[PDB]
Amino acid sequence: SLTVKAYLLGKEDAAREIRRFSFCCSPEPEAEAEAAAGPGPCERLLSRVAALFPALRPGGFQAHYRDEDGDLVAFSSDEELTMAMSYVKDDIFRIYIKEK
Amino acid sequence: SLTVKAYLLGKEDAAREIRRFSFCCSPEPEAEAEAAAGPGPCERLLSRVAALFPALRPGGFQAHYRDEDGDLVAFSSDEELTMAMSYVKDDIFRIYIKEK
Amino acid sequence: SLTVKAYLLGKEDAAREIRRFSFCCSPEPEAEAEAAAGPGPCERLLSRVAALFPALRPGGFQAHYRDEDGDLVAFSSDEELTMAMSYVKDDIFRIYIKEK
Image (cartoon, rainbow over all chains, first blue to last red; front, side, top):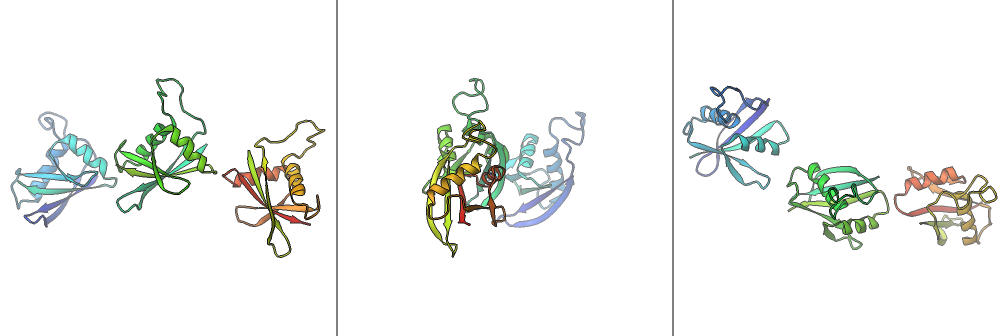
């Protein structure tokens, strides 16, 4: 299991709302194309953040993760998630949620 | 055998991570050009420090060794390694790792 | 080659005389019983210290080496020399000479 921490950013980049959800270490929830048609972790995470942060649009936001440099990188692909977890050594995945 | 101690330096030149690896007294691991195409000790050391210090880039760092004066000298050549070991009398080779 | 540093101690354990000699990394100078009849490094070292420190008796002194604890251990056997060198990492062997 891996708890993912999300940080909501308003206009002054100030923490509006905080919420976390339990995630599986598994690559993807489903295997069939009826349930995985390419993505998996990204589409899963972006789903929870939507229901968790109703303050903004359901799918009208980008999640930005810090890199080795610290800069924000708006991720939106499973390939980018596998990389983002490579940074964190612990079982906590922090990310910066922003509404488009 | 010769244990090499590496010191990771952040922004405040503070010891981020410490890790050591066992090295051979031998000049080079391999002799064939398929395995030694000029370098040997430098390329070997820089390889371990990368896998040992994943906190930064794999090959985007410079290792600086103290001299007779004490100043840091970013080494990156086998010829420089043979010299660096000439300073230390013991079987412990200390070096200052910094990410570019 | 291995330079051995000796420290002469009077009555107040104060450094009377200082002198060094070049030694070989080899186990023993000779192999024949006419030249090695058991000892080798101890008998060799104790020989030089005598000629080097004429201030006292030729063979009426004990050489004490620091241990892992720091305490002095009057050595007088080849088996004890091989161990004493195991402490020093460098190519310098320090010892405390005392006349009996």
